[PDB]
Length: 115
Image (cartoon, rainbow, N blue to C red; front, side):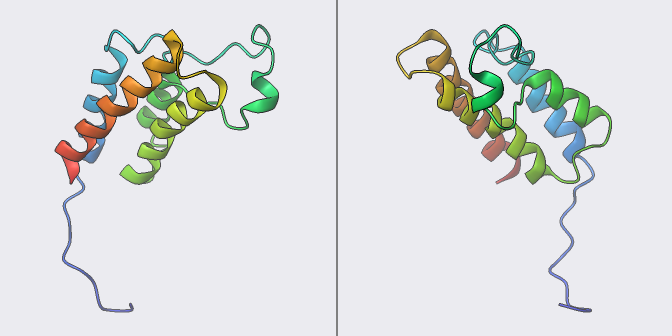
């Protein structure tokens, strides 16, 4: 509350560390469905079904322009990529498996880096 604060966690490396995690995600061999925005002209259904499209390049641009207030908002956009993938793709599909793999990958790096 007012004038009563928990001890001050150091957040000054968070930007760099989130950038590193993103680089590791960008360069994974299963990243290919998530590197660029889905082409909303050429993919039927996507515009209507996926209310909040997200992809790594868009995450990269937001990161680099100071559009993430904190590391929790960054984790939400990353997760949103995989939740979107689950919504639109069958589990038994190259793209569906890519999403489950990439989620696992991210979640481990995140815990190892911050928890």
